[PDB]
Amino acid sequence: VPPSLRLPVIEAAFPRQLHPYWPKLQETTRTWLLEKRLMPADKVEEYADGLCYTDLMAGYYLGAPDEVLQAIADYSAWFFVWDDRHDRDIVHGRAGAWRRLRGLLHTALDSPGDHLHHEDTLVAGFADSVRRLYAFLPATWNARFARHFHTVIEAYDREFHNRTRGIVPGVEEYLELRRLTFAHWIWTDLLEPSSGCELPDAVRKHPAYRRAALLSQEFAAWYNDLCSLPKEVHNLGISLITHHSLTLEEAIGEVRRRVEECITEFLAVERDALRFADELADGTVRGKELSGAVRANVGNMRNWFSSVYWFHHE
């Protein structure tokens, strides 16, 4: 809605979608936060009720089973909390507290059960949400998710050593890192349980599927940095200003153009990926299943765009 944060293409071409389960989603999530004691009451209130953070997921994973959606939103809520601890350990120098948390998250990620009632709340909460996401598809999917999140936490570690030492990463260095601390591939994985199917490595690694999955995440990551730029360390504008010596009203234009480019590139590959889907329906049953899944996944990749865009303006 602000002029400098406005994207006419999103407004004209990416209608908001809202999952039917959204009302209960907020409730069950705020309830869960209290259950697991991951956050003070006041903060829970403003997270799920005040700023309705579960709406982010509710405009994203359309067609997801209610229980799958709930699991996702819990994870995302936990994520929020972890993101707050990370930030806190940083402005405290709690490198010991942080390192041990890091080691434990790695541990829990591989064996969630053993950690459901672990002393550290953040750890037990995480382990519950992970354990729940692990109950929808084959262990191969579960294994891929862990392999992806292991990297995410390591990325969060490097960002820790970046923001203490006060190291502003190179332009490309950050871009690579953000794909990780933003958990691009976790979200991409979570599309699959939503559509009730683990895509074969072949299907999900098709140039169009993977490029579409990527642009969706880039847009979300870079629009995030655009909104938060004037505020200010980690941000695409900050990296541009520091290493390309760009100015604010310059780095703001560059990030903005890069965001706009994600939209129009996605429009292009989106079409490639839906062609791909059409082709997957060979006539067989398994084929029609693979076609619908990819299609629902591309649709949610498209939904991320409006979900993230409109979330920021509310």
Image: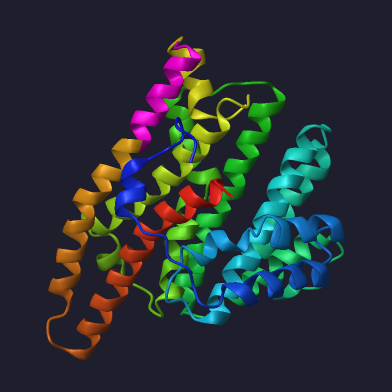
Q: Residue furthest top?
A: 245
Residue 61, above or below 156: below
Report the predominant secondary structure element of the magenta stretch.
helix
Please indicate whether residue 201 sits to the left or right of residue 163 in the image.
left
Where residue 86 appears, x then y in whole percent? 72, 43
Where residue 245 appears, x then y in whole percent? 46, 9
Tell me the residue at 38%/78% (across/down).
Answer: 197
Where residue 212 appears, x then y in whole percent? 29, 53
Image quarter of residue 213: bottom left
Q: Which residues are magenta?
A: 246-259
Residue 290, above or below 211: below
User: Does the segment drawn in magenta span residue 255?
Assistant: yes
Q: Nearer the viewer, residue 235 or 154?
A: 235
Please indicate whether residue 152 sits to the left or right of residue 93 in the image.
left
User: Does the segment drawn in magenta span residue 280?
Assistant: no
Please indicate whether residue 189 sits to the left or right of residue 150 in the image.
left
